[PDB]
Amino acid sequence: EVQFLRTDDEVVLQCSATVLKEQLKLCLAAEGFGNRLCFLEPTSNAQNVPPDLAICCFILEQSLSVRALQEMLANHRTLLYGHAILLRHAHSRMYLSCLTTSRSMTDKLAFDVGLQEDATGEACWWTMHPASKQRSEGEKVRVGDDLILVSVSSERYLHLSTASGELQVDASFMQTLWNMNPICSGCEEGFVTGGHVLRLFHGHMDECLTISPSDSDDQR
Amino acid sequence: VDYLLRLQESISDFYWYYSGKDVIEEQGKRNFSKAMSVAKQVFNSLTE
Amino acid sequence: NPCGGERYLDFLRFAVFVNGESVEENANVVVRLLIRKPECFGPALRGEG
Amino acid sequence: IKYGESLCFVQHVASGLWLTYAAPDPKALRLGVLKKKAMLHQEGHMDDA
Amino acid sequence: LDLQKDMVVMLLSLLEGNVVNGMIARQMVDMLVESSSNVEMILKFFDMFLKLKDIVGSEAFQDYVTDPRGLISKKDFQKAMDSQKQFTGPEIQFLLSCSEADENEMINCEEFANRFQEPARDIGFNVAVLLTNLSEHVPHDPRLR
Amino acid sequence: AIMSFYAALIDLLGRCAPETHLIQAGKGEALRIRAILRSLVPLDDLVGI
């Protein structure tokens, strides 16, 4: 069976690089508070070192056609190729956006990618385009598809940059293939799901599992 | 079916273009009418 | 090939500019095409190097 | 298996690798060639069929 | 409206020869559920423009009607709709907009009610047939009920 | 030849720039195109040339 992405779903944006001839998968991550810039969190070595996935999760708030988005700016739906999407950081609740600044020494035409507090303007909207002829515009986006994100405001691709020593993410005129891997779609009410933050109580004795307070002698 | 999907997307684009405007002008009306005639023929072909 | 590049740029200029005013329909299309093929900007305006 | 309709993934039986296309050749535009070298990979791509 | 009729005829043709819990019927139900809000708007349009004919036929609204010419004012029309309670406020506003009032805010009901009766009826009947067919061939769908 | 090519490219982009009346009207497309052109050509480079 084929699964389609829908609004209000949680996703991770994943890209692939080749480092020492070994495939490495990376997820787009951002802290939001104290640092709005997006970076890449590797996820290929998860069996040895767990990745920091709490900050890699994005919710698909809206999906509109370009004309509808233009009308809205002038003023659960399935995603379709050629639509514009709005991605909200799950942790900070900011919005993925193409920034006007740039800290890239290698590329003069590139822009920084980060989070912005509000969803106003066209800087926080991205258009999805198929990576291959297998898919066509207006076709529903299927889980595991390869797509290209184009910034509406800057017309630049969400691009993986390897020019420097390390792997960075920016908005440039060179394209990169991204996977919108689903994390959760809809939780049956009252049921536990992975990635949730909770407390583990000792039965019902009102005792919880915890660590020692800060500055404790046991090093927490 | 593929041509019908293309035509439907074009018609949706036209509707979104004219959605804000209070009234549709004569040229827009003529274009809408032509698109609808083609769509009608395509639907009849599928029914056949 | 700067010479051929200049010839094609001249044609595009005449396509986009008419009677002292910019034709928006042509200008937007030309700009989008140029950014979609960045090599048209020449090696100097190349992003990477 | 049907001609045209069926979509088939080719797998090397002994190693389990999948038949796919190698990574895009650098300076492909300067080459002017659309050939894509085929290879056997552990993961492949979504359009390998 | 004619184009919509042709599309509905195509859907019925798809349903020709259907079986109970047939795959085509289930897929059509899924498509309708996916387009639920727009289907709701279409049904509301047809239902409103039949209920308005019924209301103008009704004598209670004609009591609010006072002008000897039979044309009612916008405020009188609004009050009559409110009294009948068949329409909510946004709907009342919509029919007021479609009323085609004159420069004197006079609504010609004898034409307002009849404007879309003929064109609507065909598509309305075809949509009713489609819904009945789907309901009788997919009897256990909460979305369809 | 190189100087002429770059001069022709800058001339074409400038002619592609939107009109002032569109800018005042605040058309989103016009503002976006002007932003793209400013991204392409820095002001300090123009002043230096």
Image (cartoon, coloured by chain):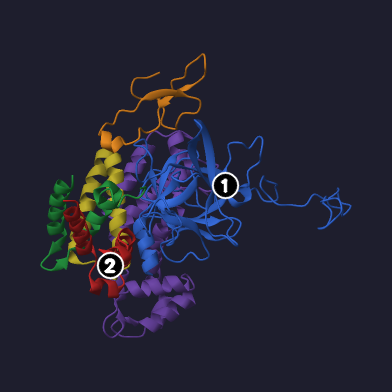
Chain colours: A blue, B yellow, C green, D orange, E purple, F red
Residue C40 seen: yes
Q: Is residue C28 left or right of residue D12?
A: left
Residue A12, position as x, y percentages in the image: 54, 46
Amino acid marked by disc 2: Val
Residue A2 seen: no
Number of marks in the rendered image: 2
Residue nearer the viewer, A157 or E136: A157
Disc 2 is placed on an element classified as helix
Residue at mark 2 shares a chain with residue at mark 1 = no
> Chain ID for label 1?
A
Crowd class of label 1 (few under 14; some 14 to 19; many from 20; radius 10 Å): few
Q: In which quarter of the image is residue E80?
A: bottom left
> Chain ID for label 2?
F
Amino acid marked by disc 1: Ser
Residue A93, position as x, y percentages in the image: 57, 60
Q: Residue A185 carries which label?
A: 1
Q: Which mark is residue F47?
A: 2
